[PDB]
């Protein structure tokens, strides 16, 4: 009768989800990754190029990963249907492999003994949630497979909600200037499904499609047809920034925009949306747990109804924190039985 | 009876202007830079981290830089009033130091012997020009000091002109995702006039100003109050991209946008504005001489009146070619 | 009765081998890569983040890649035994996939119709060659599967040959400061066989084992037991540098070392070993076709018998040129029938 | 009756020295930097691209920088002779500007009121110290201006001492693969005193000098003529690694090398020299306070008398901690 968590895919998100669970006191009972044995998991969790050394103890024994004296079972399965989730008492599962994105693909975790699945990416069909925006729409009795959307959606949606509710978004287009990720290549190589994404990640500014802005209209249905966008991948290893250009229905002097964002940050979006007026740059958000940090000085108003709003996000770390927040939220709701 | 060019500030722009002049047959008679001696100028011109080795001969002798057998006088002065422009026959001067941006600061070149000055950046008061957009407003009678605007302005203005003339820009905002430059720092250091610009250039996405925010509506006055924008400096050493989000007056389905850009690129803006449908990334424009290369596949439309348009530019190389094109244009008009 | 070439694995080396063949007038009859279709091959060959746009025409039609009007057959096979080399008249095959490194693995090309194979990497057992060092040891009648060693070996061996023959190498240890490659990761990810190599390539200086110095003693047997070394992978996308610290038998004033290197560069190692006294840095060798460029000003002599010698190499481009040179050499020798 | 510290040059080293002082309870009474005002110092100290946000409070008021409630006077002088060190009670001064390296240049601090000066770089003439190697040679009677050598010297000297004392270094040569620094350039620009250092720092592997080449045999005189080396600057923003290739007198099988380093790290060089057998890379040492971290698995031996030894260092952070350790050592010795 406590939340327990299983992680499938011990990657950037998977490992940082474990870090967040340790920080928040969420019990992780098992990790599955066929490419990382237990001894190697210790190394990959202990040392991080982006987020530093884990501040605590990491060891292995008895085929287990032991973090701050918490024993975590380690499985080595290539397919969700192979994973023995029943053995660790039917945990809530984070699907962070990147390759099981549909209800059908993720449902094999349920039949292998998972109580619920949270897909750590947009899904073509599983219901999507962004904490601070639409988590109340989760239904414990009808949804065992959900999605926590993307990092970009988690940055954009809270800001879009604040702005739309105060001023009215008539239409908006967004760009994210985004750090490279594990799907990209060190040098020019094959990416048949998205050719630009094969090009050397460290050498290039790379345009890339993203459903993340429209995704904000799955989580904020009033914005259907009113928001879309795209990405540029650039040579930084973490932290990204949303640039939202929108036309507003009611006049929105920039002072009124700042006040609305601050009010949201201090109140209902505390911990999700933050507000700064400092002269920040991307590294200043390494390790930041917010979904969206509004950059007051970087935005521009052409006029009272046409503005460019800028918001930062640690795409690895903020998102991993939201995965945990969504799990905890789901569990508190699922207690409705 | 012929165009001759002097360069003040033998930097990224100054050296690439000399390369462009060599490519386009324009005679450079002198280069001034107090921080680079002739023998050192050979090395800095011969080897380039971004644009490769100079394909030709580079030597020094008799206090001169010699490129492909052309002798270039080398001066070593810290202030424009010190430079002996009269000794090399009153050249047209490129002001590419970054620190003499006003008519007042640049006029010292004229009184030191320069025939004309082209400031290689936006100016608070000198008239600004973008080839393909407003060069015809140059008035030989009354403009001895001019500006070639900025690299971003040279990318944005040709595209904005095409879109505005075809569909009508009601309002627009732009971003440039821009390579780092010489004003930035390798590691966090002082930049009291722009604090974010001091932060390590290779480590950060850095919000910043763009010269295009102010310059674009000087060169296209009809857009005054309808367009501005900002930059993010990112960890690439050259090539940048404009992302222009605009609301349009006339219906602008994306097929019509593509046909409008193509027409401009094949016609009046040939050599200035190009058009691609290839799956391009920033390195694909290293050494491209165009001002603006419209990326058809990267753009997105929300609807027929609200669109995001993407256009690339080699911020060092395209702009340097435009400096040379402006000089040749001025010289031809000065014969009136 | 002309050299014809088949490429297996159209990667950094595979594509740059095709560029070199075009430059040198070597006929490439076919390319095989299961991850790159013909239309996508056009794109990957045309545009290069490191070496610029291909200067010529690239098109596809009739299931073929057409470069400067030369038609090249394109195959899409995952295993060497699947490739129809007989269909294109028994070419000499470049094995540049990175995954068929042994005589046994590469021999399937022979049974599929390849006349010879050149493995574009060190082999555990195929005989290895470095142009300018030991190519004369190739035997047309006994070797159908050979190796062109590695980029580092191709840089080190020519210099080591010059120095050993003039002064005598008593012992030497080398480091290569080397650009990242396709085997590395954009962000921290799994590399179970070599853990450091999983760490983000763009963020880190990464120590990495290399058999490349000892490899110089397979190609220069007199140096057995006398040379080994290691690598640091660093955040550049191409071009690397050898730093060889050696104790010499005969006194070797640095002026005598420079003269020996120059004599080799102007004479028997022309096109293989070059010599500069300019104030060069890594980008200055992008596109350089030499195996080894000796940096006169960067080296140090502690004394007449103990020195550190520095030599540059474009690891992608120089090596790709040597693959072609070795093919042409093999073919001229194989004419012995 | 207590150590007080003044910092001249509030740069990478100056700010990280203030961080180290805050961590180690050392009182900083003043900071001087003509290029950073108090309000700007708050920002530059609070936010760090490499080492993260300062974990504490940072404010300005009354012309002062206030860190965790400690008031620090802020001066704005361009020359040491201008700095009012007497106003803050004759502090021990860190000279971390990079431009006052000689006894003669640094002595102006003494005549302006400094009790002592620690130059944060090798000096042509001031006596140089490496903690764990030769600090005992400091003579309070006769050394008011000293140097803490360089970061590479602080990595190399402790390891060289251990190896030489155990096995005897016959001869050695070293390389440091070193992160870029503030002296380097974002894009190819002028560096007339060291041409390769002008080339774009983020694009290139750059051969360069290391302060350790000359400094190591000043701090370990027994190695004079037996050790020198060079650097390659590469595209990382912090952390560097020494690669020491030496011929040894006594048999040195690699197991014995490991036991010798371990013994030093656990004993007399605790906090200075560390020892790891983990599969480490450069980022793993961000924020490490040790001078030298021996990488057991990365090294290689050709034979029992010829070996290559690898040791890491956070060039910014480890060195800044050593500056503070040297100041505290000097202060304790000055009580004699
Ligand atoms: N990195 C980001 O910024 C980010 C942010 C939000 C969401 N996401 C999403 O999170 C998911 C993972 O992203 P990542 O960045 O962590 O990628 P990653 O490549 O770092 O991690 C994927 C992990 O999954 C493991 N794996 C692969 N196949 C597996 C399988 N069949 N079974 C079990 N494990 C398998 C890999 O070995 C690896 O450790 C993706 O859907 C991604 O879109 C990423
Ligand atoms: N780099 C770009 O992308 C780009 C593009 C368009 C325009 N610009 C503008 O061009 C100008 C030069 O920029 P850059 O990127 O070439 O900078 P840079 O730092 O590379 O070049 C400036 C050069 O001026 C020399 N210099 C400095 N002070 C001088 C003086 N007082 N007198 C003579 N020479 C002096 C320097 O030694 C250096 O060689 C700036 O105004 C910049 O805004 C830059
Ligand atoms: N890049 C260098 O600096 C360098 C230099 C010298 C030698 N090498 C060696 O050359 C070889 C290739 O290196 P690379 O850098 O070009 O790697 P790469 O990853 O860029 O290229 C490998 C190519 O092989 C293809 N491939 C993968 N599996 C295949 C298969 N089963 N059949 C056919 N094709 C397949 C991939 O799709 C890819 O295009 C490796 O052995 C490498 O060690 C690399
Ligand atoms: N960065 C490293 O890894 C490192 C390590 C060890 C030692 N050092 C040495 O430390 C010194 C500082 O290096 P850094 O990397 O901190 O450089 P830096 O450029 O970051 O810092 C120098 C600071 O001095 C200030 N300054 C410049 N001129 C001044 C003057 N005349 N008076 C007062 N302040 C002035 C600058 O505004 C800047 O804040 C150099 O001697 C360097 O060799 C650097």
Image (tube, coloured by chain):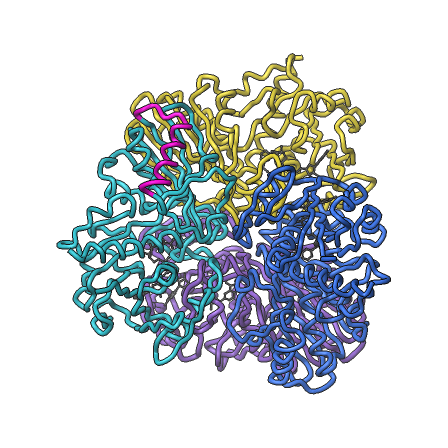
Chain colours: A yellow, B cyan, C blue, D purple
Report the number of discs: 0
> What residue range appears in magenta?
B249-269
Against A75, is C204 above or below?
below
Residue D246 coordinates in the image, percent (x, y):
71, 75
Residue B252 coordinates in the image, percent (x, y):
36, 26
Query: Mainly helix, strand or loop, the magenta region?
Result: helix
Q: Which residue lies furthest to the front in this view?
A: C1
Is residue A175 or residue D55 the one in the foreground? A175
Can residue D178 be seen in this snapshot? yes
Where residue A170 sits, quadrant-wise, is top left
The residue that appears at 69% across and 52% down in the rendered structure is C196
In the picture provided, is D58 more to the left or to the right than D155? left
Q: Residue furthest left?
A: B141
Is residue C151 or residue A245 the one in the foreground? C151
Where residue B185 sits, quadrant-wise, is bottom left
The residue that appears at 30% across and 54% down in the rendered structure is B325
Against A337, is C308 above or below?
below
Is residue C116 or residue B240 the one in the foreground? C116
D335 in the magenta segment: no
Can residue D64 be seen in this snapshot? no
The residue that appears at 64% across and 74% down in the rendered structure is C309
Is residue D217 or residue B35 the one in the foreground? B35
In the picture provided, is C160 more to the left or to the right than B277? right
Against D32, is C279 above or below?
below
Residue D82 coordinates in the image, percent (x, y):
31, 70
Residue B233 coordinates in the image, percent (x, y):
42, 47
């Amino acid at each position: 009768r406590e939340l327990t968590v299983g992680i499938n895919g011990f990657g950037r998100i998977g490992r940082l989800v474990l870090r967040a669970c340790m920080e928040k006191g969420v019990k992780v009972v098992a990790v599955n990754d066929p490419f990382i044995d237990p001894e190697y998991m210790v190394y990959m969790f202990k040392y991080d190029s982006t987020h530093g050394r884990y501040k605590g103890s990491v060891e292995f024994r008895n085929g287990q990963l032991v973090v701050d004296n918490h024993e975590i079972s380690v499985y080595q399965c290539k397919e969700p249907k192979q994973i023995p989730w029943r053995a660790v008492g039917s945990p809530y599962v984070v699907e962070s492999t990147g390759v099981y994105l549909s209800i059908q693909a993720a449902s094999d975790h349920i039949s292998a003994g998972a109580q619920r699945v949270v897909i750590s990416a947009p899904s073509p069909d599983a219901p999507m949630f962004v904490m601070g925006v639409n988590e109340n729409d989760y239904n414990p009795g009808s949804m065992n497979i959900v999605s926590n959307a993307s990092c970009t959606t988690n940055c954009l949606a809270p800001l879009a909600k604040v702005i739309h509710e105060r001023f009215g978004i008539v239409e908006g287009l967004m760009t994210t200037v985004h750090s490279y990720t594990a799907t990209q290549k060190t040098v020019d190589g094959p990416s048949r499904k998205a050719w630009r994404d094969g090009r050397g990640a460290h050498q290039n500014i790379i345009p890339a499609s993203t459903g993340a802005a429209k995704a904000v209209t799955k989580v904020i249905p009033e914005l259907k047809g009113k928001l879309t966008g795209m990405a540029f991948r650039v040579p930084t290893p973490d932290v990204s920034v949303v640039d939202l250009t929108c036309r507003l229905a009611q006049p929105a002097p920039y002072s009124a925009i700042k006040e609305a964002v601050k009010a949201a940050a201090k109140g209902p979006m505390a911990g999700i949306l933050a507000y700064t007026e400092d002269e920040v740059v991307s590294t200043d958000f390494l390790g930041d747990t917010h979904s969206s940090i509004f950059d007051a000085k970087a935005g521009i108003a052409l006029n009272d109804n046409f503005v460019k709003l800028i918001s930062w996000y640690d795409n690895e770390y903020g998102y991993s924190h939201r995965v945990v927040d969504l799990l905890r939220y789901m569990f508190s709701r699922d207690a409705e039985n």
